[PDB]
Image (cartoon, rainbow, N blue to C red):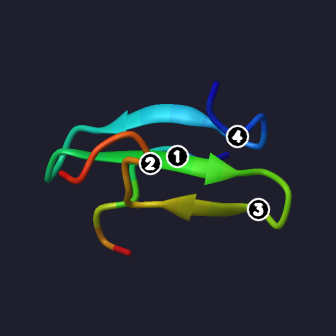
Amino acid sequence: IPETPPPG
Amino acid sequence: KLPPGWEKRMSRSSGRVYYFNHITNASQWERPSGNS
């Protein structure tokens, strides 16, 4: 599932 | 009126649209309708 990229 | 390949959720962290193109399947940090 795609959500919430910040670390990458 | 944006790309139908879009997966729409906001990045609550830095203030980014993580807008994920489920064609190749990748999440963009980006906003295509803005700059930041």
The residue identified by callout 1 is B19
The quarter in which the N terminus of chain B is drawn is top right
Going from the N terminus, do you reach mark 2 or mark 3 first?
Answer: 3
Dots 2, 1 in contact, CB < 8 A: yes
Mark 4 neighbour class, 10 Å CA radius: few under 14, some 14 to 19, many 20 or more: few
Q: Residue at x 61, y 50 (%)?
A: B20
Q: Residue at x 62, y 33 (%)?
A: B2
Measured as percent of width and height from the top left, residue B5 is found at: 77, 43
**Label 4 is found on which chain of the structure?**
B
Q: Residue at x 70, y 40 (%)?
A: B3
Q: Is residue A5 left or right of residue A6?
A: right
Mark 2 neighbour class, 10 Å CA radius: few under 14, some 14 to 19, many 20 or more: few
Q: Is residue A3 left or right of residue B7?
A: left
Dots 4, 2 in contact, CB < 8 A: yes
Q: Closer to us: mark 3 or mark 4?
A: 4
The residue identified by callout 3 is B25
- Please tell me if label 2 and label 1 are on a single chain: yes
Residue B3 got which mark? Answer: 4
- Please tell me if label 3 and label 4 are on a single chain: yes
**Label 2 is found on which chain of the structure?**
B
Q: Closer to us: mark 2 or mark 1?
A: 2
Q: Is residue B26 left or right of residue B32?
A: right
Say which of B12 and B22 sits in front.
B22
Dots 3, 4 in contact, CB < 8 A: no
Question: For the residues marked 4 and 2, what is the alpha-carbon distance in whole angstroms?
Answer: 9 Å
The residue identified by callout 2 is B32
Mark 3 neighbour class, 10 Å CA radius: few under 14, some 14 to 19, many 20 or more: few
Question: For the residues marked 4 and 1, what is the alpha-carbon distance in whole angstroms?
Answer: 10 Å
